[PDB]
Image 1 (cartoon, rainbow, N blue to C red):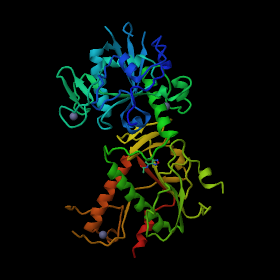
Image 2 (cartoon, rainbow, N blue to C red):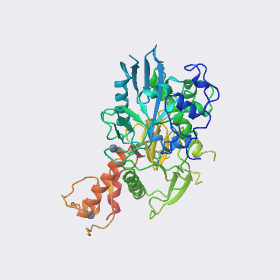
Image 3 (cartoon, rainbow, N blue to C red):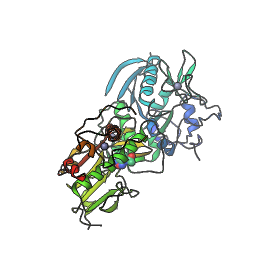
Image 4 (tube, rainbow, N blue to C red):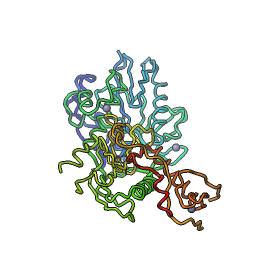
Length: 459
Ligand SMILES: CC(=O)Nc1cccc2nonc12
Ligand SMILES: [Zn+2]
Ligand SMILES: [Zn+2]
Ligand SMILES: [Zn+2]
């Protein structure tokens, strides 16, 4: 029960307008065959072109919505649309390209998928709302066979060249002409009433329908992400390391300790209300304060309404002391808050486009994150960069230039000259901080917060 049996039934009702007469009784086996491919009863790690929902969820980074529209089937030109916003026109002889034969179109398809995917995934998963032309177009740019490795590396093969008769991964694919051993999922098999737009638009106002192949491709992927990551959430699914996941996570731990430790020293709150992950630990364990936890799972859909977190009757008095929202996304933070809030608009390899302006942030786990909203922060200000240490000035054991900074808040800087230890630590913390920011996190704090109040914690 790992792979999708090719003897599983495929509902063909979605297909019968592009493919009139299609049998109601249909297997993957007979569909793959009808699509022009032969599986040759092959036990070589590619049991089925089509995959389960579970397999698709584990391979979310590989998702490319795909849609084909009859432009006028062998007779007529086809519009190919990918969730990259690319539209290509194939002739049998937002980006909108003119009509060209398949022999060139297949080259553009390999280049596009390779650039999109080489830093995301070892494969492609075409995400479909299958009506027939997409499935019957695959033979013109897809070759299948046994699992293979790259001719230039140890990564599984995703592309094939008819020029050289060789196989490459996404990294090594330049000049290759065929997609090799793609995967695919038909969203329409999930049990939906009515068309794509009627179903997409239930959940998302951000993607319109210009009635072009790339728009349906985007809607198809959006609806899929809605179904697998918004409405359904699984924090048991691990995802591979593909970037700076580990540095970013370490940075997050170090900034959080820094910022909260400073806020407590600066304003000496008698109570901190820690609102979010039910697994959360005291980020400043030595701090004098009354630490009070409130459980909230990450809101994958709409931001939490502060009315429903706080009221319905705790310390009850969240207006006492300070509220810590560390990636606990609410509509409008109270004025007495420390906040980390993920900016869904960031471009990274970790952040995939999501549903209704939100984004899918994949780092160990997948977190669909509601659209970043500036109005949430109206009672707060941006938290300026600073470094604070009360640790003793003492080197122990990295070559030096003397550090000069207004934001190095230490005894040594108070004394006019930053010691080597605090300068190493300062530069390390600044690097962590820059990592986290560029990874798309944003920091906000109560308006009264002033690093000037930290200097008198040394006397
Ligand atoms: C620990 C972790 O990766 N959590 C998160 C990252 C990005 C956005 C999030 N929204 O809630 N939790 C989020
Ligand atoms: Zn390679
Ligand atoms: Zn959408
Ligand atoms: Zn020092």
